[PDB]
Amino acid sequence: PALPEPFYYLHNFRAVLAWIGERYADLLDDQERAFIAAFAELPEASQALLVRMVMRKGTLFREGKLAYAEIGDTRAAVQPLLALGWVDAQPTLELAQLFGLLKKDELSQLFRDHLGRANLRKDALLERLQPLFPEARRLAEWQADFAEPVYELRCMALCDRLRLMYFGNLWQDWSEFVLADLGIYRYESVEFSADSRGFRLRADVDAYLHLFDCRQRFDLGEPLEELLAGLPGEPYANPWLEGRRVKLLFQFAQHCEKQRDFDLAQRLYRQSSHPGARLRAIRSLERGERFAEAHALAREASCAPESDAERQGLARLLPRLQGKLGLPRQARAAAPEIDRLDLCLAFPSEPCSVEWAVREHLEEPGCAVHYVENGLINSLFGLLCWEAIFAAIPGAFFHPFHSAPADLHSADFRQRRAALFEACLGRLEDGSYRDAIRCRYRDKFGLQSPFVYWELLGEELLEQALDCLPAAHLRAWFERLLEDIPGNRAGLPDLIQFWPAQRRYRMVEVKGPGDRLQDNQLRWLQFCREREMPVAVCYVRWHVDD
DNA sequence: GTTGGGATTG
DNA sequence: CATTCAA
DNA sequence: GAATGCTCAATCCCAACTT
């Protein structure tokens, strides 16, 4: 869609280098400063060519796929990069990499004397020929008549280290700059300290890179024996880093449980503080026929549960373990009688998921039904509390592209922000919360945020929600979300219906045939019907006339 | 000729 | 989380 | 009662599939 400067991407890259120079100046090593300075020495076209290679996929390129008009002649622009070693000409290629660079026609002809196989695909061709050609070669040693040179980028690790230093993570690309400049991504602007940055110590960057590496190798099928040997056993000082580690241990354990190695899964879950891990360790011990440990851990956990999810899970585990130890059957109570509404509806032909069906059936004159499912309540929260969620609390925002503060999932996130929350939530006690939300809605429309789904929240659903929802219910929900954000942001009922005449609402969780209530949904039903909130669960059967 | 997936571009 | 498994 | 399969559209290139 034509940004006016043909070098827009190079401009952005220079912006990141400068930014890292001022904010990270104390964290950079010798190789890094040499890279930034050397890059500043490059002629514009070689700078541009570099950034082009960095932003594309993989490290290997054919000269002809590197044509660009701002740069002109590619060979000329690449020569200064060859002199620094940041690009190899004539690298050494594994057969698979040769297969990445080459067309299937060229490859079919090249090895034609070893192909009697069949007409068959490219990946199969690679498979058949790999036991034949294990030894890597330069491109010239593969075929000497191939007339297009091939370049390999050699600085990608140092670039990824720069990316992660600027963004505080590796998932965000440099195209963040162009997508925000084009208005495809619109981020809220925070004014944060000129000393604000993602990483404090160099070793914390080093560690993020090590965990990231570990996840990569695991995803490639590496045995956990050397994976675990490589991880640190001791927990990290930096807590947000210990989150990454602890998540990784968690997935290792899940993989183990899949392999039915229950003792190791238990071990790995037990050394992780990841939310829900203790539960998975009890359940793993039970699966490993280790009942006494499972029971012990379950009693430990029930003394001081981590979450409501953990309370609910122990409620099933404990009695089954008690039974497995031959302990007396302990009396319990029935579920709090979910308030249910049965519907027998036409068979659609064709589907038409069931939630749309109930939503149609419940919509009459006078009744408005919306398929929202925790997007409306979270949105109302994010609108009211916007000014606290985006507060300039130090270390919460270090660059223009945050969709959420960095500490959003930290334990004292609310404490750090305390006043500003009881300010915002306070507007629920006077009348001002409606106006405040409508203005925040108009001001902030489209801005990326953790809790506000704008696509879902049209002006009409906003107005009906505002005038039909009690403020005290809003406060109840909003405090429940704040208490544990990541465990409570999901599970609200599929539908919500409004009767704007009498300003009334009811939420409806929809369940088709073969559908049952998840755990979080059940906790939200319990929470709602302890407030005498209007929730109902709707179970649907289909009618086929024959 | 003709789709369809993935890399690329702004 | 929406399909499969267990009596 | 429980075990498990990081968001844009428009465009260009290359593999696969028709007769």
Image: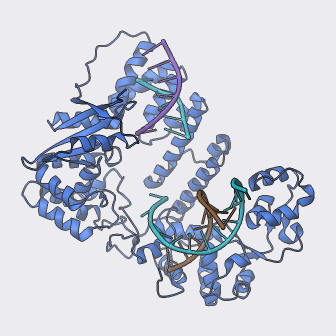
Chain colours: A blue, B brown, C purple, D cyan
Q: Residue furthest right?
A: A113
Name the residue at 39% across, 10% down.
A327
The part of the image, by quadrant, that contains residue A303 is top left
Left or right: residue A481 compared with residue A78: left
Q: Position of residue A340 (x, y in %)?
A: 23, 29
Snapshot quadrant of residue A326: top left
* Residue closer to the observer: A339 or A430: A339
Horizontal side, residue A274 vs residue A435: left or right: right
Taking depth in this image into account, of A189 and A236 the one nearest to the observer is A189
Q: How many marks?
A: 0
Left-right relation of A449 to A35: left
- The picture places residue A70, in percent across and down from the top left corner, at 60, 88
Measured from the top left, where is residue A386 in percent x and y?
25, 62
Q: Residue at x 77, y 51 (%)?
A: A124
Give the residue at x 32% y 49%: A485
Relative to A292, does residue A54 appear above or below in the rendering?
below
Residue drawn at x 72%, y 88% as measured from the top left: A76
Whether A309 is drawn above or below A105: the answer is above
Rendered image quadrant of residue B2: bottom right
Q: Is residue A26 visible?
A: yes
Rendered position, A365 above or below A301: below
Task: Give A339 or A239, whichever is nearer the viewer.
Answer: A339
Quarter of the image with the C terminus of chain A is top left
Residue A49: x and y in percent read 64, 81
Q: Is residue A308 visible?
A: no
